[PDB]
Image: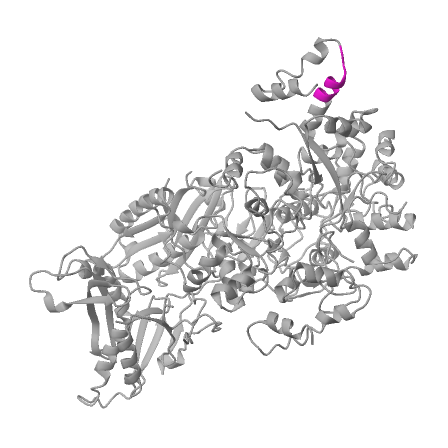
């Protein structure tokens, strides 16, 4: 029994006619930085088992084409900045925490036809997330109870460091590495010479005990057996 | 990466009169694998009356490769083609056609097809390799008056491709007089990288095309004194014998090509080194200087004006060829050329005067490894009492892991440790002292056969690797390796390197070397 | 504008009253070319890329076969010059074949003929916009907007040995510093600090295999390696120069114009060229800083670039020493 939930953020969607308790406002203590932002969830099929899939693939193509107007020109209209970068911001940790907010109330309406619990996040991110301290410690304490979380990256391009990592966003750049998460990459199907591990874009114009770089990392598969059974 | 997917001759296109395939199993004059056998036509196949196929590497679906090759190698209009299918299979295709019944441009029957000989490669080819396959196919597919599928040449060709990396060459090489680099470089490629055609066409001073194969021969069924004049010091006699072999015969070359072949042994060492790994050196000049007795008019003419419109007119205009004429015109032609070889060319006394005058006036000098005498060419510029020598490319042995008493680091004067008069710089005699003594007679050239891998290391160390591995700066490593030859205690001080090869400190061997220095 | 396409065509094996129909956009899909390239445009093996050569040019093509009852079979071909690169135009044609497959399995373009006529302005906009800039965003549905990009397909990079030196040919101040990887942002500050084994434990504190991979990828895009910068020569200094000593051999070594062991002759015998083409050095002290460590502008690049506008000195300097 699946859900397929799309989620994203926008920046500078401050206010319009009665759209006030929808916004949020992000900030940084050590260097002052505070902006307006807004989180959107669009769900596709909520709680429905059926055989003969791949019709969701057609509906996700329809929603991909409809998506930028669907996210940009809604509730508040200042100057909009859509769909912020994952390696700079993101609502990732809040999304996993809301999946836990679903799964804590499993005893409410009990299907007699399901046993196991699973939450999979597909991201085009690199593996970097810039995450507040309190939410990360809180989700450690909540995955203490019922470990259900799986992350997979369809960006590919397995970087040159310990790839699941969090730069802290607390109210040296403070790193952290999780050992509770199950990350897996998805390489595409082709054969060429030297798969580069770097992007590039040309502009016009006491302890410090975890660093992330001296940890060695060859390849991570997909782990299909922990995604089908 | 020089691999071999397929060389194939399929009877895909038999459109002719009589006595072959037409609707029976595969069958031809002097070759009939028939009565429904395994049916091979491809590369690695044991071949006689009866035959056996093998399939090794094409990185694709091999029966699909055969069944698509049948219908995807025939061309209707003549010429030679190329087909790059998927990312890692190519086919440099060569058909030809001779359809005529009893025209023979006597036999038992006309069995003549659209010819179907083709060899392949995967994904990183080279236009030299393409030209090689074009030339081999042009020489294979000629006529064969009585049609003969001689597959023994197919087996020699399949061994030819994997066996020998280089196409064709000669141990006996000629010379660079005044004319040979121009005679090379004006078309730059006459036919199929043929040293023998190159030196013969320059040797008779005229172009003549008698064919050259790769390693299996396929037939198509004057002496001037200037040669021995420009080739006194290096190889006149057997080169004149090769002139005799090329004015007389063709294809009968490997009978006379190779079997015709302190100070004396070092001369032979210079020959065995010029065969592979040591280059020579020359110098040139140039007339370029200036900013915002017979030097100031040339300087003014070069400064406020262009040159050849002015300084090429006055020296006959006063009826005196003298120091300024000899400084103006022949030195300007030598500046057009820029080796010292035209100063050797157009002279009778200038050779002892020319650098004297270049030091006399303000001409700029420089010294260089000589112009474009690449190892795809024969051998240049014969040895004399004056030519300087230095080796660059060829590798050599190793010093620090194996802990030889012989110190061989490649530093300044590259290999640090009546008597070689043509040795201009220290690397020549340092390399030959690192090779061997001058005492062994034939075991010395056996050791020159042995220096491939140089008593079997490969040198991954170039005298800055020591500064990479540990705290060996310039001073310490030179003070230790300048008396390394004598006693190996100074060697073993670094050559106890197993102890800092089993470091167990997981960060830095430099500090552990610095601690293990004095104890 | 290196590669230059000129004609784009669709074709289809028609039912028996027609052999094979074509939809052309401008070369020309003429008679004899299509006759002699007929056997490639129907194959046993499907869904693979295949290009052939011919007298005028090169079809890069792929065919597909669907609707096996009255078995339907079409192909998209992309005909370009005889000898251009055309290694950057294989995945674009294969990706267009994949898009046409999903377009036929969702909405069935090539069973109705008004969409078959609509298929031709697709080719005209592609033929304009590939040669225009090299990428196409092109909507043809409520559920398909085809996207295409020309990848330059650079050659392989060499190996990055443990003792070389990176140099930026380009400038660091032209990129987004925020748009890199973390390892590149932790290497890129001390990249002028020459020795690789210095910079790793100077700022990086990384695995040396990791900084090797990172500098190899920066060599694959935009950074040139060279060999170490210990003061080999000392005796080049007795000529008068206007503050032009350090970057000189770094530039001309980056030009790949030397035998390596510079000794004591290279610098003077081209420093006469540098003098006519135009406190202390503390020279005993750059030695302990060399193991692992836990006129206003000086004319060094301006003169070589403004004479790189000409070519005589780069002939006389490619001819090395």
Q: In this picture, which residue range is highlighted in magenta?
A: B320-329
Q: Residue furthest front?
A: C279
The percent position of residue A87, horizontal first and vertical second, equals: 33, 65
Q: Residue furthest top?
A: B318
| The N terminus of chain B lies in quadrant | bottom right
Is C61 left or right of B157, judged from the image as shown?
Answer: left
Residue B267, visible in the rendered structure = yes
Q: Residue at x 42, y 76 (%)?
A: A209
The percent position of residue A118, horizontal first and vertical second, equals: 30, 81
- Magenta region includes residue B332: no
Q: Nearer the viewer, residue B269 or C7?
A: B269
Magenta stretch: helix, strand or loop mostly:
helix
Q: Residue at x 51, y 59 (%)?
A: C215
Q: Nearer the viewer, residue B423 or A224?
A: B423
Q: Residue at x 41, y 76 (%)?
A: A207
The percent position of residue A172, horizontal first and vertical second, equals: 38, 68
- Magenta region includes residue B326: yes
The percent position of residue A57, horizontal first and vertical second, equals: 28, 67
On screen, C164 above or below B421? below
């Amino acid at each position: 029994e699946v859900t397929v939930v799309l989620f994203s953020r926008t920046f500078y969607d401050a206010k319009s006619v009665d759209e006030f308790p929808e916004i949020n406002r992000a900030s940084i203590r050590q260097d002052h930085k505070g902006r307006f932002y807004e989180d959107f969830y669009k769900v596709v099929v909520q709680n429905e088992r059926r055989e003969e899939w791949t019709s969701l693939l057609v509906t996700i193509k329809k929603l991909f084409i409809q998506y930028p107007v669907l996210v940009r020109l809604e509730q508040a209209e200042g100057f909009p900045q859509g769909d912020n970068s994952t390696s700079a911001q993101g609502n990732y940790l809040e999304a996993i925490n809301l999946s836990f907010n679903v799964f804590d109330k499993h005893y409410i309406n009990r299907n007699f036809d399901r046993t196991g619990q699973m939450s999979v996040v597909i991201t085009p991110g690199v593996g970097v997330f810039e995450v507040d301290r309190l939410l990360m410690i809180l989700t450690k304490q909540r995955m203490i109870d019922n470990g259900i979380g799986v992350d997979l990256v369809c960006m590919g391009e397995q970087p040159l460091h310990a790839v699941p990592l969090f730069k802290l966003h607390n109210r040296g750049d403070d790193y952290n590495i999780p050992h509770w998460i199950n990350h897996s990459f998805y390489t595409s199907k082709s054969q060429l010479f030297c798969n580069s591990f770097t992007p590039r874009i040309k502009l016009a114009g006491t302890l410090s005990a975890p660093p992330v770089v001296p940890g060695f990392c060859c390849t991570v598969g997909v782990d299909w057996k922990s995604l089908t059974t | 990466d020089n691999t071999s997917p397929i060389s194939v001759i399929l009877v895909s296109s038999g459109s002719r009169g009589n006595k072959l395939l037409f609707r029976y199993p595969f069958q031809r004059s002097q070759e009939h694998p028939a009565s429904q056998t395994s049916k091979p036509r491809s590369r690695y196949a044991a071949s006689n009356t009866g035959d056996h196929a093998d399939e090794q590497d094409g990185d694709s679906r091999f029966s699909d490769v055969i069944l698509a090759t049948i219908l995807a190698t025939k061309s209707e209009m003549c010429g030679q083609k190329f087909e790059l299918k998927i990312d890692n299979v190519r086919f440099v295709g060569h058909p030809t056609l001779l359809q005529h019944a009893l025209g023979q441009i006597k036999r038992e029957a006309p069995t003549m097809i659209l010819f179907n000989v083709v060899f392949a490669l995967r994904a990183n080819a080279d236009p030299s390799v393409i030209n090689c396959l074009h030339n081999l196919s042009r020489r294979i597919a000629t006529v064969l008056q009585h049609e003969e599928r001689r597959c023994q040449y197919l087996t020699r060709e399949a061994k030819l491709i994997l066996a020998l990396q280089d196409e064709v060459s000669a141990m006996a090489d000629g010379n660079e007089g005044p004319q040979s680099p121009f005679h090379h470089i004006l078309p730059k490629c006459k036919l199929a990288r043929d040293l023998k055609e190159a030196y013969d066409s320059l040797c008779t001073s005229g172009v003549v095309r008698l064919h050259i194969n790769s390693w299996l021969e396929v037939s198509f069924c004057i002496p001037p004194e200037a040669i021995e004049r420009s080739l006194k010091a290096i190889r006149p006699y057997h080169a004149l014998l090769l002139l005799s072999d090329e004015k007389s015969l063709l294809g009968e070359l490997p009978i006379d090509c190779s079997p015709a072949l302190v100070k004396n042994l070092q001369q032979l060492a210079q020959d065995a080194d010029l065969a592979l790994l040591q280059v020579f050196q020359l110098a040139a000049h140039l007339v370029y200087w200036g900013k915002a007795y017979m030097l100031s008019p040339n300087a003014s003419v070069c400064l406020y004006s262009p040159l050849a419109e002015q300084f090429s007119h006055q020296f006959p205009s006063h009826d005196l060829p003298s120091v300024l004429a000899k400084f103006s015109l022949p030195v300007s032609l030598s500046e057009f050329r820029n080796p010292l070889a035209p100063a050797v060319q157009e002279t009778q006394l200038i050779q002892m005067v020319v650098w004297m005058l270049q030091r006399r006036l303000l001409i700029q000098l420089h010294t260089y490894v000589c112009l474009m005498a690449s190892p795809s060419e024969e051998e240049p510029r014969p040895r004399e009492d004056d030519v300087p020598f230095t080796a660059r490319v060829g590798g050599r042995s190793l010093s620090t892991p194996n802990a030889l008493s012989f110190g061989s680091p490649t530093s300044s004067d590259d290999m640090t440790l009546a008597e070689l008069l043509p040795s201009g710089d220290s690397p020549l005699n340092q390399r030959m002292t690192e090779n061997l003594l001058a005492s062994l007679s034939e075991h010395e050239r056996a050791a020159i056969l042995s220096v491939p891998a140089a008593q079997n290391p490969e040198d991954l160390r170039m005298f800055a690797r020591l500064l990479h591995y540990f705290r060996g700066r310039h001073h310490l490593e030179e003070i230790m390796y300048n008396e390394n030859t004598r006693r190996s205690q100074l060697l073993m001080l670094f050559d106890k390197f197993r102890s800092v090869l089993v470091v167990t400190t997981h960060e830095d061997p430099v500090i552990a070397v610095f601690q293990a220095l004095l104890p | 504008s290196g590669c230059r396409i000129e004609c784009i065509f669709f074709s289809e094996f028609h039912p028996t009253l027609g052999p094979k129909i074509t939809y052309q956009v401008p070369l020309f899909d003429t008679v004899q070319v299509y006759i002699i390239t007929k056997p490639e445009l129907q194959n046993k093996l499907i869904t693979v890329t295949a290009m052939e050569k011919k007298l005028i040019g090169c079809p890069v093509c792929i065919e597909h076969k669907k609707y096996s009852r009255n078995a339907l079979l079409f192909n998209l071909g992309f005909v370009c010059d005889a000898q251009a690169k055309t290694c950057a135009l294989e995945p674009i044609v294969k990706k267009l074949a994949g898009y046409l497959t999903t377009l036929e399995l969702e909405s069935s373009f090539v069973s109705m003929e008004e969409s078959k006529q609509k298929l031709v302005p697709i080719m005209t906009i592609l033929l304009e916009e590939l040669n225009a800039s090299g990428r196409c965003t092109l909507p043809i549905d409520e559920s398909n907007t085809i996207h295409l990009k020309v990848i330059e397909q650079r050659p392989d990079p060499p190996v990055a040995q443990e003792y070389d030196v990176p140099v930026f040919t380009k400038d660091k101040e032209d990129f987004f510093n925020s748009q890199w990887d973390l390892t590149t942002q932790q290497i890129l500050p001390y990249i002028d600090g020459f020795r690789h084994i210095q910079k790793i434990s100077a700022e990086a504190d990384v695995e040396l295999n990791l900084v090797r991979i990172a500098i190899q990828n920066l060599l694959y895009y935009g950074v040139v390696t060279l060999v170490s910068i210990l003061q080999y020569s000392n005796v080049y200094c007795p000529t008068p120069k206007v503050q032009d000593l350090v970057d000189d051999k770094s530039l001309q070594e980056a030009c790949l114009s030397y035998v390596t062991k510079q000794g004591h002759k290279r610098a003077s015998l081209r420093d006469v060229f540098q003098l006519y083409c135009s406190q202390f050095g503390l020279m005993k002290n750059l030695i302990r800083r060399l193991q692992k460590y836990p006129y206003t502008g000086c004319h060094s690049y301006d003169e070589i670039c403004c004479k790189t506008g000409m070519s005589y000195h780069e002939l006389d300097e490619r001819l090395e020493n």
